[PDB]
Image 1 (cartoon, rainbow over the protein chains, first blue to last red):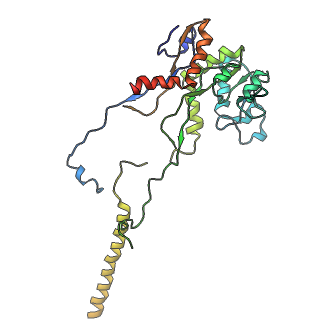
Image 2: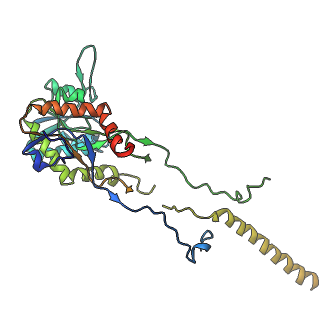
Image 3: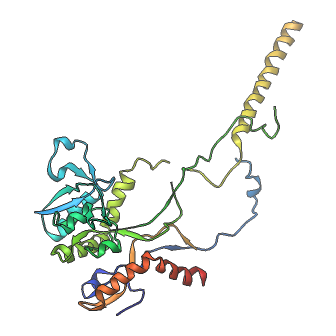
Length: 50
Length: 130
Length: 95
Length: 50
């Protein structure tokens, strides 16, 4: 028996048997914390819109 | 010609606009209605879309120990297959066979899509009172 | 509107009588449809594409300009008021 | 940090040799564990708790 994060694929379901999914997943996006700040020279004005 | 049982639940299986002027499988439209044609194409078979009598999914009356809805019509030979939003539960997997999930879901939260805007006139002035 | 992720993991499936001939075939068919993105396509067709709500934007959060703008206008009422009154008083009072 | 929902729907499962004796038992076991919230519990234990 195989107990691991084995993906249930068609190519494999043909040769072996897969139990029902014990964990549903997919493809996700990973970014970096957007904590940055710049003072610039335009920012100041901005609370009052153009 | 395979007997496909399904429940009337939008937007999986709904009555087409001019369903009164139509017959057979053309009467219905929806996610499962299309999913049926797809399954039938890859498995190679003709089918007849039929709506479950009692209009239930699958449950089991404790007393009579009788299955109802689509799950019922399967166990008692009324239908050959069930193409609908039928939840894959342990209690059902024991009596019938469930293919791999064609749609993963769960319990969600519904709130009023909030209105973020309530501009006044002088709320401009409201920090002070008349 | 729906908020946050699901609370549990469920899933619908095609039900077939125990020990049926359509059993394995249909199973593979579902897997084939999902990999071809046909399942995702169907959902998009009936949920979002066929949907009536793609309109219901802004954000970042800005200033109050509205109420402020009422102040502009009424303020202008003051303007034109000074305008005419002063006019007819100059030319008409003097003249 | 992960942003937005998944791009596709996958899932891991317990693999067993075609026509094995452990085949049905394990299958039901996975379903039982998920309904008892034991699977969700395990994930929380190793992902967020730990």
